Amino acid sequence: NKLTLDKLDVKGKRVVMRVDFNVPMKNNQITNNQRIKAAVPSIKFCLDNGAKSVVLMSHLGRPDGVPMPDKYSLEPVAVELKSLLGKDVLFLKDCVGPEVEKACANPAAGSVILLENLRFHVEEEGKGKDASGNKVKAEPAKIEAFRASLSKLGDVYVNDAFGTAHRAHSSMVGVNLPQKAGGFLMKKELNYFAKALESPERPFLAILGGAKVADKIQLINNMLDKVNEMIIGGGMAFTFLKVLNNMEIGTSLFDEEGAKIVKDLMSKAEKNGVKITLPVDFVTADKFDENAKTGQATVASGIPAGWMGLDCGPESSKKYAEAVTRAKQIVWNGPVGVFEWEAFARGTKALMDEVVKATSRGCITIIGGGDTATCCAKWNTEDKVSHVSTGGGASLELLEGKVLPGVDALSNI
Ligand SMILES: Nc1ncnc2c1ncn2[C@@H]1O[C@H](COP(=O)(O)OP(=O)(O)CP(=O)(O)O)[C@@H](O)[C@H]1O
């Protein structure tokens, strides 16, 4: 279909490799390195297979096309990468231009080079904001030059940046080398998602959680065409409960736009035979705070208002468990409560326990990136589910049935 790294001859070749090293940070300290580790297999393969160089490029955060070295440098990533790889990483303070080109022209065999944040240049995204905060547009000649420069850095191109595969950015689709190969991470991610979406083992359970409904309509709709069961949890559930069940939800999140289509979505489900599991009980809070006073409510009792519901309750966890038990395949995108806070994490943790249990008995368990992946780190379960995705937005696009420009741009095999 598409050329992949396993099929690519890299011996004695400089490999310029787009990766997603857009890792969570604080005070320029990396807080989850999951994205970095995820790329190691492609990098090692290249090295073990005689690549002259591997030049790594990524964005970090949204500097919006202006240099932000004290907020968004990849320098910390170069440090973490050397540790993961047990090899030196040469960090360049830029990604394009004559000095970087000189550095990458003919490196000593086995050289690993990490470029500075691609997004310090407006050319990468093709638009951005000026240093005064005004929206600005990249210029075509400059974009071409930007792409040309990156292109100079390797003989062959590999994209392992699954997390960025939804972005038609210069580094992702604009590289002007004839051989453009998907990396092992890109391959792995797509395989699990394809199987899940094209050819699932059944029953196929989707667990969708999150705050709002409006932004998930395509996703729910598409998933309803694929799955056998769906759990809808988190903040989004209140919209369904209020509309469908007449529930009193207090101050819990309510999506007015979403409420308009909830019925239509449930109709599709019924028509398709998809069993919907909504929460039946809740952990309530008197305010939206980590340390709020908490209570308990049922759909029938209502949320006494305007208290808000911030986790599912024990009976919900039981129904969720029952669904998990039924499943031979699961895709989980979204926590079922405010997992960030211990008083409202219980539902999420229990579900994680169930998902882990399912994996141990052969359930194919796919965790969407973003918050759900974060939970995997938090509770140390990355090696206990089948797949923890590195791409939240990207994975969501696939789940919505969308094409990834980063994949499309690869060479055909
Ligand atoms: N019952 C509930 N009430 C309010 N918020 C809830 C909730 N259950 C979960 N959440 C919150 O939902 C958040 C995730 O929701 P959402 O739909 O906004 O994804 P998101 O904010 O990650 C989109 P983006 O990718 O831009 O960050 C988590 O931060 C969690 O605290």
Image (cartoon, rainbow, N blue to C red):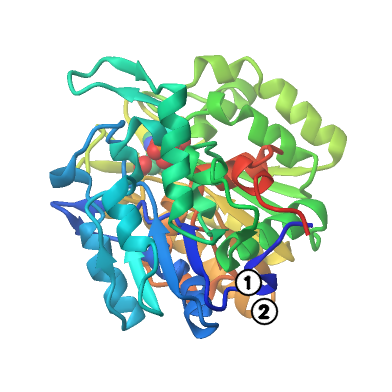
Q: Disc 2 on helix, strand or loop?
A: loop
Secondary element at image label 1: helix
Does residue 155 appear to the left or right of 95 in the view shown?
right
- Asked if residue 289 lies left or right of residue 108, the reply is left
Q: Does the residue labelled 1 lie within 8 Å of ligand 1?
A: no
In the depicted view, which residue is nearer to us: 300 or 180? 180
The disc label shown at residue 145, or none: none
Residue drawn at point x = 28 percent, y = 55 percent: 342
Q: Quadrant of residue 406?
A: top right
In the picture of the structure, the residue carrying the numbered disc 1 is 358
Neighbours of disc 1 within 10 Å: few (<14), some (14-19), many (20+)? many
| Residue at the (43%, 48%) spot, across then down | 150
Relative height, residue 247 to residue 3 (above, below): above
Q: Can residue 296 be seen in this snapshot?
A: no
Residue highlighted by disc 2:
361
Residue visible at 17% across and 18% down in the picture: 132
Name the residue type under label 2.
Arg
Q: Nearer the viewer, residue 215 or 129?
A: 129
Q: Which residue is more in the foreground, 353 or 309?
A: 353
Q: What residue type is labelled 1?
A: Ala
- Compute the Cα span from label 2 to label 1: 5 Å
Q: Where is residue 212 in the image (x, y as percent from the top left)?
A: 49, 29
Q: Which of 220 and 391 is in front in this view?
A: 391
* Ligand 1 - quadrant of the structure image: top left
Give the image location of residue 294, x and y in percent: 28, 43
Can see residue 308?
Answer: yes
Depicted 217 relative to depicted 224: above or below: above
Marks 2 and 1 close (CB-CB < 8 Å): yes
In the picture, the quarter occupied by the N terminus is: bottom right
